[PDB]
Image (cartoon, rainbow over all chains, first blue to last red; front, side):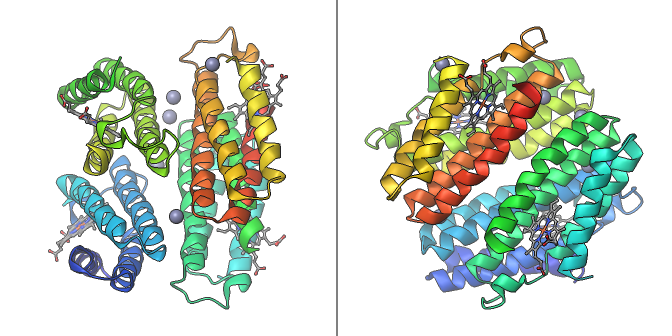
Length: 106
Length: 106
Length: 106
Length: 106
Ligand code: HEC
Ligand code: HEC
Ligand code: HEC
Ligand code: HEC
Ligand SMILES: [Zn+2]
Ligand SMILES: [Zn+2]
Ligand SMILES: [Zn+2]
Ligand SMILES: [Zn+2]
Ligand SMILES: [Zn+2]
């Protein structure tokens, strides 16, 4: 899917997690986030469209998604163990990484 | 391609790195490894065919590739800077990740 | 030093990195941050003062410094190669680890 | 404790883990390993006695303990949750990191 769609999927499911009531909702939303983040990993954002794929900017862009995926996986673990409140708190730590990338490449 | 072909790629290019003389040959091998691991991401290993694609086991399986890809990209940095022996030490630690996943899922 | 001093050292030197324009300044600040984080390793934060020093919580507390120390080292590596902007890009994500520990434990 | 003593602690407690019957023995052993590795983190090994603490060798030596501690932390987490066989298996994957460091610096 394209980057815009990946971002709407991330945004939608992050807000679901914030408001969910059960592990199943949280796990389902985190699974969708993991897939959208892993898909966006290969994207070229408009700010960097003329940069080399080997460029430091793009390496930093891809690193941001690697970080985000690792955080999503950790939240998924917490949810698979039924620590819904801990998984929801982790989702709030996700936002910082979202914002870190946006503050640079949006 | 499929997981088996992805793994042949990882194995072949790990051997290239070990015997390499120059940084470009290590960079080339690591780049192919990175591509193979990203393609293996979507795969269902035989030992997990009895699980749902969103099961804890399948997310842990993909987390192994997340680790591997992080390490591959660290070693690619070293190679891009001319540090052949340093990249070769990193590949020794890469094998620990190969083995750890194989211990659980191969 | 104690945790209160270590956090001032982390915060002061993070601000130095944010305003730096040369690699020597960034390298100096990151080295001080690494020392402070290593020193903070042994600390017990007030909200875990009732927990055993090997509860899941205290190992998880130390793991937060383990993440930070890894990120500091990565940024230090970049500074040692003269890549100010790349080092400063890494300090921004560093901030999310500060925040994440504070969210759980401050 | 000195580096040799740290290494005896690591080796003894790795064997305890392989021989354990319950999660509490595995947890106690990993706790001892986490502490000994964190002590060893700041040591200078005989092989690197004449090297700059800022040398690539010493950076790589310290990084090896950073890797090992992260692995120990992950195994301790598994044991704490009653994934006893997985914790024992992870401790068995520590050896690859031990050996990778020994190859270079012992
Ligand atoms: C880089 C590594 C990013 C991370 C991590 C996250 N996002 Fe993102 N996002 C990024 C870019 C480059 C852009 C701009 C896309 C463009 O075409 O200009 C965006 C955009 C968004 C948007 C707006 C999309 C739109 O249709 O206008 C949203 C809502 C968004 N991003 C959300 C979001 C969330 C919730 C994230 C973490 C969970 C997140 N982003 C991470 C780059 C990066
Ligand atoms: C999990 C995340 C894995 C990682 C990381 C690596 N491998 Fe792997 N490998 C994995 C599976 C599940 C399988 C079985 C595939 C099947 O259909 O049977 C394999 C298989 C291989 C092979 C095939 C030959 C064999 O002895 O089985 C090779 C040559 C191989 N793997 C190599 C390899 C290397 C070098 C890796 C790291 C660089 C590596 N694998 C990582 C799962 C995972
Ligand atoms: C570097 C990053 C290392 C890691 C990780 C591990 N060890 Fe180690 N080990 C290292 C050095 C430099 C030395 C030599 C110390 C000396 O001064 O001679 C060692 C030594 C050992 C020994 C022998 C100790 C002795 O008294 O001679 C053992 C039994 C040993 N190391 C075990 C061990 C284990 C089990 C590890 C991982 C769990 C491990 N070491 C990690 C450097 C490093
Ligand atoms: C846990 C692993 C932490 C990490 C990582 C960081 N900090 Fe922290 N910080 C932590 C705690 C438990 C506390 C509260 C301690 C207390 O006695 O109440 C703090 C506090 C701070 C403060 C406030 C200092 C004060 O005068 O009260 C600052 C300014 C601060 N922390 C900064 C900071 C920075 C910049 C970090 C990353 C670079 C960082 N902290 C990481 C625990 C943890
Ligand atoms: Zn790179
Ligand atoms: Zn768990
Ligand atoms: Zn470098
Ligand atoms: Zn000591
Ligand atoms: Zn270094």
